[PDB]
Amino acid sequence: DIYKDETLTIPKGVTVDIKARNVTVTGPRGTLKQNLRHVDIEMKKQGNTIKFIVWHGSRKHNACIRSVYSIINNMIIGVTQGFRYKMRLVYAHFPININLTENGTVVEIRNFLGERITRVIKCLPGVTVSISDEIILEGNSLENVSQSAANIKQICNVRNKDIRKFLDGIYVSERGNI
Amino acid sequence: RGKRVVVLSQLEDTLVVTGPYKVNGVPIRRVNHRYVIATSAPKIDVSGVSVEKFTKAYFAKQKRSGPVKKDEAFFAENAPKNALPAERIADQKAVDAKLLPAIKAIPNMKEYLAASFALSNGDRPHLMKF
Amino acid sequence: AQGHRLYVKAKHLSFQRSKHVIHPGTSIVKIEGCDSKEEAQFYLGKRVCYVYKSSKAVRGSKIRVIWGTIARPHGNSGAVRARFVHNLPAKTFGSSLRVMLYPSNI
Amino acid sequence: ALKEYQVVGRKVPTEHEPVPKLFRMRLFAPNESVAKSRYWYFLKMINKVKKATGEIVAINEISEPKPLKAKVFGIWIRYDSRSGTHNMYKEFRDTTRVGAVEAMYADMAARHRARFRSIRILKVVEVEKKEDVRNYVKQLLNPHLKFPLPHRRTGKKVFAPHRPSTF
Amino acid sequence: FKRYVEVGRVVLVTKGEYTGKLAVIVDIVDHKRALIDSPCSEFPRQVIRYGSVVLTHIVMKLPRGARSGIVAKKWKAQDVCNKWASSAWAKKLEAKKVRSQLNDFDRFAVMRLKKQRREQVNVAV
Amino acid sequence: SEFQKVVVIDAKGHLLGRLASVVAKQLLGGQKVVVVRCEELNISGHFFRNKLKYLAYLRKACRYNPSRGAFHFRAPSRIFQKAVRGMLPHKTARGQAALEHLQAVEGIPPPFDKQKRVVVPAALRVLRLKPGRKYCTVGRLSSEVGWKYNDIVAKLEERRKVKSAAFYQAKLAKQKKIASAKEASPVNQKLSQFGY
RNA sequence: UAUGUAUAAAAAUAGAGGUAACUCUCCUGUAUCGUAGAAGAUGGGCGAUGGUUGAACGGAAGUGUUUUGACUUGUCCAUGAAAUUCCAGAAUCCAUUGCAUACGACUUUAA
RNA sequence: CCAAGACGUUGCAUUCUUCGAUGUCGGCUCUUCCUAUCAUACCGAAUUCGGUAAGCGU
RNA sequence: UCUAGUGGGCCAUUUUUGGUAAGCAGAACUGGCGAUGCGGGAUGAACCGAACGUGAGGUUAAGGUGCCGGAAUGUACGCUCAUCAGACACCAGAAAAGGUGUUAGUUCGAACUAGCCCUGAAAAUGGAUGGCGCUUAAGCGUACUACCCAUACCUCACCGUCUGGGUUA
RNA sequence: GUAGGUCAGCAUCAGUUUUCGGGGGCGGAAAAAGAAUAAGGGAAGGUGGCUGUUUAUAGCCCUUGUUGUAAUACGUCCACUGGGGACUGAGGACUGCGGCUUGCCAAGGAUGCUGACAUAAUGGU
């Protein structure tokens, strides 16, 4: 269509400036700088409302408008309240040992399924790890927190064994805000 | 080439023309009409100057009818000092006297006639008008 | 030094040719600032020349000139066809030419 | 550049048909020669008339009565494809029937690779009611229409000195 | 944005026999064509494509599909003439046209006058 | 329109083929061309497709003496010269003379960072691609096929940009003064009838 | 191969750029810098106090950038031009060495 | 591809050159390419069947 | 009237027979090549256009105009994104059936229906829309202008041949 | 004075051709439109007014009249006309066909006015 628009109201967040389509959203919790060069959308800021508009876009290009609205709300939620993931360890026989170094940006996993190899993972920037067998992933970027959970889950994978019997692994339990 | 001149009269084929000799030093000469760019500058009054004595015979060269020519003394001959008749000088001075007052009256034209036309970078003569 | 150049700068592009057959009798010339055949109409019939320099002194001159005339426009991009008294050497492709303002009609 | 032609013709009279019927057709063709050709093409498929045993009794070039007024045209066509089992209805918004047919021919060739020979125009009608109107045509009929200027690539002017503003 | 293709926008024609003229979008035919009109007699009402016009900053209040007389009446009432000229964009365009119309004697006068202008180069130390 | 003795071209935001076509024609016209910032050139199409195209080009080699076969240059400026070479008749003496009239470089070296850099709108990506179409950068394409100076070119570029920014402020300060003194002269408004 | 061999921000392009949450500009260079004078002569009167020319910085290829006797068309004026009378102290050999070697070459040494 | 892996359906001799002669099997030797993958690496299902894959060996 | 050479043909259009098929064998009609250069299809004996004395100018055919390459990086409206796209007849090759790819349609959201893309698709020296490259194209479909140029056309000069008309001064 | 080497420039013409411009006749629905101005009709993608309505504090659409022998566009034609560029100059007293007023002429094929160099300048190998 010629005009497809979505409207969002901005919260009390400090700066939402969009220089070079790059949203440098700074709020009470922190700063999240992300690019919107992947979408060709006129989003206009006036007063306390922002309008995402696409002109002459087809169905494929018009589908990304709601995705932009979803993500723009996402780091608004991140810079206001933040994102926290609670992730519980499941093991049958061998307890899983987890160590956090330099305030949790590196997580070391040992004794997974009885293996002697130490699995060390570097979390994405802006995410910190804490021990509540519960792991808490808190940060500003939902992108980085979810990715860090994905990396941990993929790293603690069972190989060449029957999943039907071996239910060991690490799966996310709760995804909420601080 | 590049001089600015004032047309006196139209001869059989060319134009009898002179940029005032006291302005740019171009004497009375015939110039073929295909080798001039006429300008849109304000006209100079040439009604008061005699143009009947400027003819092909007046500008005619001396007949030679022989292949012998050229010499260092030959080049030492001719020149403005020699050759140039006093009557030709008087005619140049007379036309100057009858032409200068008009270009004095209209501003900037005296020094315009003194200057020399030239093309510069980016100048496109088809777009340019004179 | 900008009180001269009563000519317009041009470049010898190529001979008049088909895909494989050249015709060196007439040449293709790109006059600077001439961007259409309507503009080429002004330059039709002008006197174009190729000026080059030689070691031998012909009549006491280091500079010798081949003269020619713009004949017709060529294409839509302002290129013109030029006929010279001596066909321009094929080594001049990309060399410069002087297009005078005479025979003038402006 | 197509043109709308009113072509009226009849077969030549015979002893069986002393007073043959006059048949008229509105058809779009670049010139009168093609217009008469298409008239005989349509009359030949329907009503037993050659070009030889018939004649063109009237030729007229129809111009748009209101060429400065925006209109919506609904065009029914017969489309012949590699399968050749097709009827279509399309709608085009412009100021003249000739332009609507021209835009139809370009659109039909673009979207279906159909040629002038393959397409025959069933009927071109002006749609006057907005409710009677294609979704794209309706949303052009939006009273509050406004949109930015689309990209338009803006003598030889090679070697620009400054990067373009393009806005 | 500042330039929207909409009913009543003033446009400047850039391609065609009416290049350099001002018109107003009376109606929108489609995404690529629009009906425009101008009060001037030399510019008739016609359907034109957006590729030959550039959108000006001026918008006038004009009902859709207005006739030439009403468009001219609205054009005079909202005083769009010399409202376009007040902008530096129009002044630059008019300066370009005046400068292009100059002749050799005028060009020599320009050279002397700007040479008088250049000879100041007096600035505070 | 007008030929300069040497033209320096900023290759940033330009398409490889469109710019090469323009450059090759200019070189055959007898014009000396310098193209800077060849690492900032663009090739239409997404990166992996162009990566596959170059890797296919890399395979071309003689079975006897690969040192005789096609030589695959990994530098962005040498990729540009390859495109211009293929668009020139380089087996011909005219084409060779055109090739030595081209100097394509990564970044803007000191003989050229103090000179004006023009652009070719017939080859600019913003004018020549539909928005939303994927494209790649020659510099990144070069770095992941073998070019090993992408970092040093970048680091030297910000130093040049910092010096260029300092130059600009100094020139803009001068232009502010000359502009202020411009309207002070009454002749500026006297020659308003002339269009200046 | 020249004929003015004149022009250095970076960026985005569904935006920038300034001046001072403000406001102006953009919509290319057909723009700015320049351009007058025997291929540019000899003088003079006003006016301006400018203009053009014969230590530090720059390593990406620094071929530079900066810095600190002439020449006046800012503005007036007077002579002169023509008949060019219609286009043109080392290396090597000789020798030596064997870490080398088909021969050259290579590694040594030799005043 | 099809539903009842059947039935079907769609695909991956000539005598042009040489009879003023192109030395005519296999083995040995040796190098290279191909993938329609035996092994190796890494994945997906229910040792077996598969996908990427010719780097390396056979 | 006398006599030469010839009495191995081949290809294409269309029709057609033998054949699993064949750059296979066999015929019919016409046009060609052989015996024929030239413009074009990158390249080719028969494809397209046009058939040729020596030249000058003009204009076209077929085919082309991003650069190589002479000639619009022309105009108008769309379609297409291809993880080894596509790009001009002959021609130098791919099918059924699908594909939450996408753009349009038809009939009562469902099915169909088309156009492009992808899949089906798969080899051996490294290499081929001719190459470079090309993505609101320099790809595809349609429409409209301008332009380029053959030994063809037109005007003219000259050569020769043939034909016709004069010529006892 | 007469005629005369080579090479150029221009004018006035002839042949051929290309490229721009103006004026006029005629044709079509004796264009369609439109403008301006009188009737009536209808309404919206609904303005002022108060989602709904019928020109008001915007207007639009349809029909008719008028201004009208309207203009323009397009087509066609002029034995109407203004430019610019290119190539060619065959023939060699007179005849001919024509226009003009006997002479003249653009009418059975280029002459006129000049300049430079007389040179290896043109030309050849």
Image: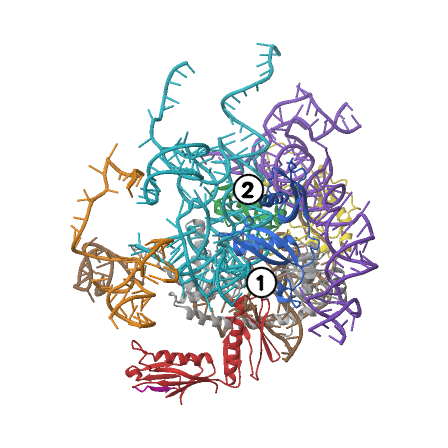
Chain colours: A red, B yellow, C green, D blue, G brown, H orange, I cyan, J purple
Assess whether residue C81 is covered by the magenta stretch: no
The answer to whether marks 1 and 2 mark residues whose Cβ atoms lie closer than 8 Å is no
* Mark in the foreground, 1 or 2: 1
Chain name for mark 2: C
Q: How many numbered marks are there?
A: 2
Q: Is residue B106 visible?
A: yes
Q: Relative to residue I20, is residue I164 drawn left or right?
A: right
The label shown at residue D84 is none
Categorize mark 1 by other alpha carbons within 10 Å: few (<14), some (14-19), many (20+): few
Instruction: Please provide the residue range marked out in magenta.
Output: A94-101
Q: Where J95 sits versus F62, above or below?
A: above
Of residues J92 and I86, the one nearer the viewer is I86
- Residue ID for mark 1: D151
Label 1 residue SS: loop
Report whether F132 appears left or right of G27. left
Q: What x and y, as percent, mark residue E23? A: 70, 61
Q: Is residue A96 magenta?
A: yes
Look at label 2 and name its amino acid. Answer: Phe
The amino acid type, in three-letter code, at marker 1 is His
- Answer above or below: position of I7 versus F87: above
